[PDB]
Structures are given as C-alpha cells and as structure tokens.
Length: 453
Ligand SMILES: O=C(Nc1cccnc1)c1cc(Cl)sc1Cl
Ligand SMILES: [Cl-]
Ligand SMILES: [Mn+2]
Ligand SMILES: [Zn+2]
Ligand SMILES: [Zn+2]
Image 1 (cartoon, rainbow, N blue to C red):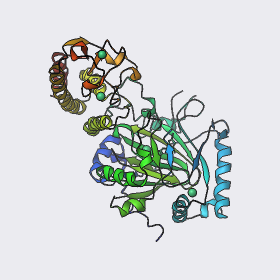
Image 2: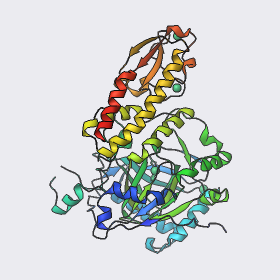
Image 3: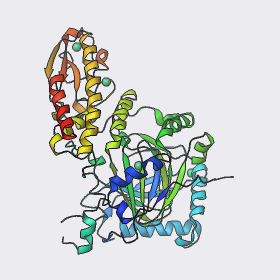
Image 4: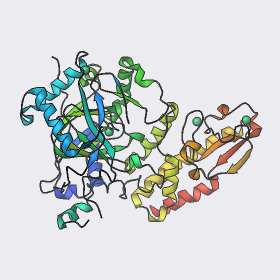
C-alpha cells in the first residue's frame, strides 16, 4: 500500500587483495551485478581517503528543481558549501519538525514518492552539479600545494576517481578527442529530496560514484537487459520525453515511481549508499534516486574492454534514433590500433576483434554505394574536422571511416547509410570521402594480432 520498496541490490565487501585492482574486481562481480544494473561496494575499513577543504572558499551556482512525477527535466544565486549546508539542514529540519538524524530513511523514501505524486504540493529544492574546475575541485587528493604522506597512498589509488579514466584497462584512455564531460569527474552537492531522473550513461558506459560524506543517497536501478522494457513503459505514460531533441544537453528525462515499473514487470532494485561507499552502474542500466539530506558525491564514466561491443551496438542504436554521438567509436578503435605496440595485450586482442567487424561492415557499405553509381573518391582526414562539421545530415552520426559529399551542397555530409539523402544531383556528381583504404586497414589489424600473440 502506498510505497512497497524494491528488493535490495547486491552488496560487496572485498578484501585488500581483491580491492587492489578496480578492473579485476569489476570484472569479477560483473556476472552478478549485471543482472541488477547497480551494485554497492564497501571498501576495506582502513581505506579512508582524506576529504579536506574549506567550506568557505568554495563557491558554486545552484540548480533549482521542482518535484513532480512524469514532469520533464533537462539533463544539463550563489552558495558556499557552508551556506548551502545551513539551508539544506534547516529545510529538512523544518519539513519534519525533527532533528535531521532522527528522520528514518524509510520515512524520507515514502515521503519522497508521496510528494512527487501529489499535484497540490509545489515543493522546490536546490542542488549542485558540475564537472571539477578551479573554482570548485575534486574531493580526492591531486597533485600541485604539498601533501601529507597519507594523501600519497591515496594519490595513485585505482579508486581515486581522477585516475580511473586514464588507466590502461580503460579503453577511453587514449582518446585524444576532448570529451571532457565524459572523462573528467563530476561533483554533486545534495540536500533532502534533491533527485536525479531515470537515465543511462552516454554510449552505454559504466559509471562509478563515491559518496564523500553526509547523509545517504537512495538509488534505484534496472538491469541492462530490461532497458527497452523500461522505455516502452515510459512511452505510454510520458510520450513527450520522446519527442526528438535538437541536441544532447536537451535530452528530456523524468522522475517515475519504481512501483509503476514493477507493476509492468520491469525488475527494479534499490540501495542506500552511505558515506565512504561506492555505487557502480553497468552498461545500459537505467537508474534514478534522491538524497536523504546534505551530502557530497563525486562520479565518473568509464569503459572496459568488456564494453567495446556494446559501444558499437550503441552507436548503431544512436543512428536509428537520429541522436548525437559524444565521440566517434571507429575513430577510437583506429587510434588504439595505431598505438598497437604499447597496448596492453588483452586490450589489443579485444580491439582486434572489434576492428574485424568494423572492416567487414565498411567493405559491404562501400560496395553498396559503388553500385549506386558513386564513382569519384578522395582520401579525407575526418579527425581534423570539428564534430559539428562532420555529422550525417540525416542520422546525425559522427563520420570517421567514410562519408559522401557533393559540390552542390558544400560542407554537408551523409554517412553511407543515407546516400539518398544528401541532394537531388545524379550519383555520378557525388564523391566518396574515406579515411583509409581497405589495404591500409588490414596491416593495422595485423599489428594488433602480433601484439596479442
Ligand atoms: O544528479 C545528476 N546526475 C546523476 C547523479 C547520480 C547518478 N547519475 C546521474 C545531475 C546532473 C546534472 Cl547536470 S543535473 C543532475 Cl540532477
Ligand atoms: Cl509535487
Ligand atoms: Mn548516471
Ligand atoms: Zn547517416
Ligand atoms: Zn548535389
């Protein structure tokens, strides 16, 4: 009646040995956690990174939030950490006429789902969300200022989240394209009821989130295999969130009761994440939640070799939906291949397999456009073009392997799936622009094969 909480998600407490290597561990729990979409990770007891900072010297600009179920929010007037905290604590304490630590988590959860479902209640809250900058930086230790020998052990940790993008079992590593939103950590300052709507990460990547201090964060999560069920359910009840958007800052997202999803047979899991705990989201796992009170978290995207085939499927899916890519997947594969001699050996074996599918798809597409009568061709270094200058006019995919142009419409490109969509000139006026000949590609792949023995 009213709110029936979803079953709890898996919890992991690894030993110092298991905990040593982030990617080994995440690869270990993967067959479990991928069935529930999210999971929680408790570090060893002696693992306490030193959060330290001035609550007075760090300023930020707050975002405002209305709390209404099925109402649309867009994915992406000054507070210090101290003045925000004073506001958040007063708010929660006045809402319940209790001292903040005495409000049971069970009750804030029930209350949250009641107030978003009621039209008479116009509750608004505020929060902070921004990538790490100089005006406001990471909660983890970084290099600059001299550091105490404890901050040193934590400085190179796998679980320091400034380090995780740029390690070498991460594939998003050697991307030289700037994808700052997706390589740098984000900082979140929460208060009671401030929330995050149902979403999946760009390019179906993993994410990892650490709560530094404060009151808990409540999460809901759906496993990757149920993603499309969840999307069907959400199209019936809020079809406005699915009207296609002019870009990627304008993706529409919403709050929705997990009981609604459970009624339509979507599996959902919950957890409360407390200070010093990690939550991990797996590829294409939908998730949402809200904060129990004043707190501070930090989070980052990342991609393992596991993910590479889903990254290809996802870019394919983006094309069907005509939505924008954050980076070119093919451009990343080729960049890694061009660094094949310094690649980790299991990485090189996995890239080579994805490159083989890439090449074979590209062969077929080029034969198809040839039989359409496109005859002229010229090499072109796509990676030098700004992204907005190389998106398919039809499906908006970011071009890298190849594209069709026409002197008729200078500057415009279509990918090889949308040759019919550039203009009305006969196909002999068109030109095939291409990064690599088939003959350049096979030696790139061979170098990968050698590296992997
Ligand atoms: O909170 C946010 N995102 C989030 C948080 C935790 C897990 N996944 C996603 C977020 C980012 C914005 Cl920009 S406005 C909000 Cl709200
Ligand atoms: Cl409301
Ligand atoms: Mn997220
Ligand atoms: Zn296209
Ligand atoms: Zn033309």
